[PDB]
Length: 264
Ligand SMILES: [Zn+2]
Ligand SMILES: [Zn+2]
Image 1 (cartoon, protein in one colour):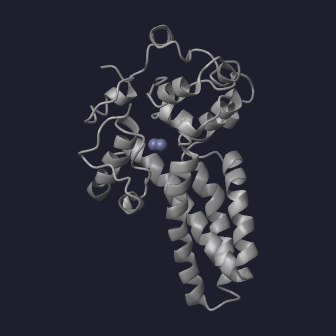
Image 2: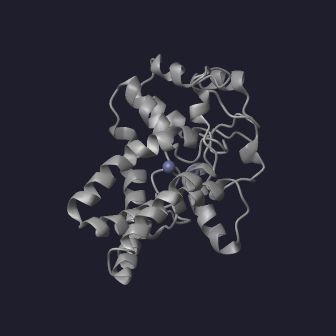
Image 3: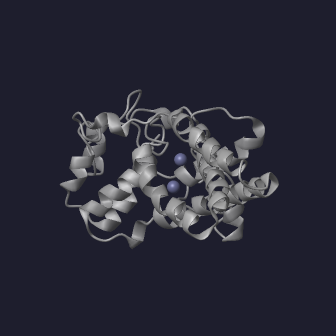
């Protein structure tokens, strides 16, 4: 019925794609008007931190189309399809890994690739938990609200927005820039090549997995993970930071079990 209310058990998948009443939403909750650009509506807002963090994680749905962010000619930048990540970054994975296999013991390079994707799983947990869900640690500033919106907020706000799920390369370049420079500073050259290639491929897997968790009927062995992450969306967002695996959730004691309570 009401999509703004969290449930202890996930409702029908058909109710997750129900278009939200715009005017009724802005009237009932006095948050954001979905019929008008959201970003400028945030930069020019009088919201308190707790109010924003409480309302943004209560999912909406614009409908068949995609919600407006800028409303002008900058809007195309905010529409990034699922197939964008592989076609843009997989060729980079291959090249970096390709170089390593031509100037280094191939087996050791393969190993460094694997540790690359492992380190990636860890980074996934770390970013998703501490960076993507900054939440209560946020300052009382609209710029911070907009930034958090761009990073991970908008996805929770409009989950079934098929063009605002994956990370736009414009942002991913910024976020990956520190990791890349760091890897090549510490590790030997071709080691850095292999390792970074691994991490990047891991990222591609992460974004693709994360997408198809929302917009596809996956094979049975992944349906558990789908239920898991969808419970991170519609039940409790203080837990279940692993999207590829709840491994780091078991490790760091943030597993989203059936005994998990609802959020505040
Ligand atoms: Zn998601
Ligand atoms: Zn999240």
